[PDB]
Image 1 (spheres, rainbow, N blue to C red):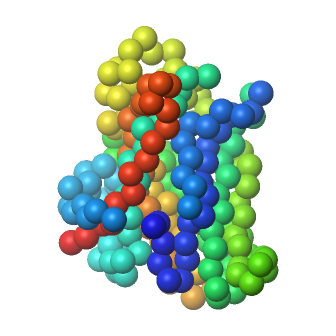
Image 2 (cartoon, rainbow, N blue to C red; image 1 turned 90 degrees about the horizontal axis):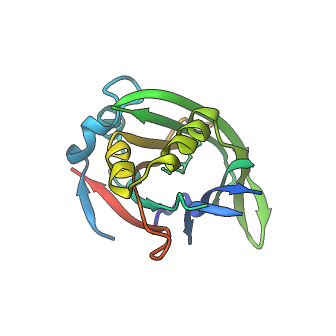
Length: 192
Ligand SMILES: CCCCCCCCCCCCCC(=O)O
């Protein structure tokens, strides 16, 4: 699914524990990266610029329909591969196409059941987002939450620390769901 031969996403979740899950991927249609250029900055570490440098098959889009219907605020991600690597993981939160947060983290492979796992677990969600979410959930209507969320996106770049090569670049876009329907996601490939 979300993956190359070199690196695959296995789980991604953002949550609040008193455990509520805003989003959750547990583990394909195309989309033209040009469609979403204005949703991320034009600067260095910009989506157009990244996609230029390649490689094209490393770039994905997740659309999330999140659950704001509910503390410790955390982000748990887990990747896997067959090669032993050290990862640089860069998450950039963007608001109206401006980068407002960059979080840079590192994770060395751990051997388990004959593959290498990379566990970035219960990382504390930055306070920009915790505050943002507290506000967002005050809103009286879903359609108002989606309006606000049309201007909010996240870009995650995962690179081989030692070689500097891109392994994965994921663009995330957001709406809210009803609690009836629950959290949902749709993974796409980015093409050009
Ligand atoms: C609108 C619902 C958004 C909730 C999900 C959060 C998105 C994933 C977290 C991005 C990476 C963490 C960034 C950081 O807090 O430093």
